[PDB]
Length: 162
Ligand SMILES: [Cl-]
Ligand SMILES: [Cl-]
Image 1 (tube, helix red, strand yellow):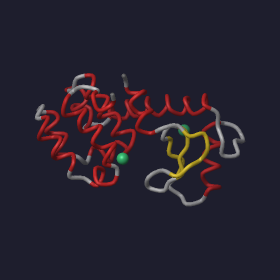
Image 2 (tube, rainbow, N blue to C red; image 1 turned 45 degrees about the vertical axis):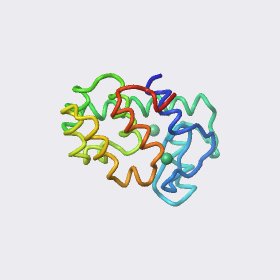
Image 3 (cartoon, rainbow, N blue to C red; image 1 turned 120 degrees about the horizontal axis):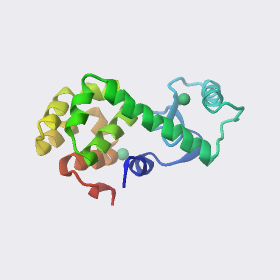
Image 4 (cartoon, rainbow, N blue to C red; image 1 turned 180 degrees about the horizontal axis):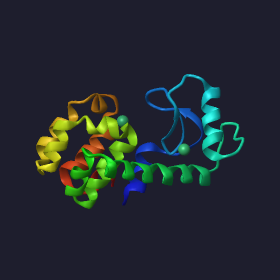
């Protein structure tokens, strides 16, 4: 298992524009297009991202390509974030994958605001961090996914994904 496989499970794969859990236009493997409520605005963002007139549909290859870019960006975003970097540097490989997933879902800004959980993670207080992570809108809105990422942080294993 690895980050890509993990996010593919959490996000799924759709070849046509769809709305995410927040009702935002998305495509592929969790690639957010726009927070705007206009489909045309989304179709436009999509053609711009793919470099062709798509008409709201892409192929698997195109989806995988946005995916690669998106995971690379998340990683690089963590590494450039003064709050996130040190936490990421302190973790083992499995747990790093969990921090990446959260950033992919919520943006680095969102994650950087889990001040207290970050500190617990950094200090390697697994059970406490899990508890704190759960007192969040994140957990209440997407509880099954959240439980998976939280167990990952708690255990350091991929069991929640098996
Ligand atoms: Cl893009
Ligand atoms: Cl969920």
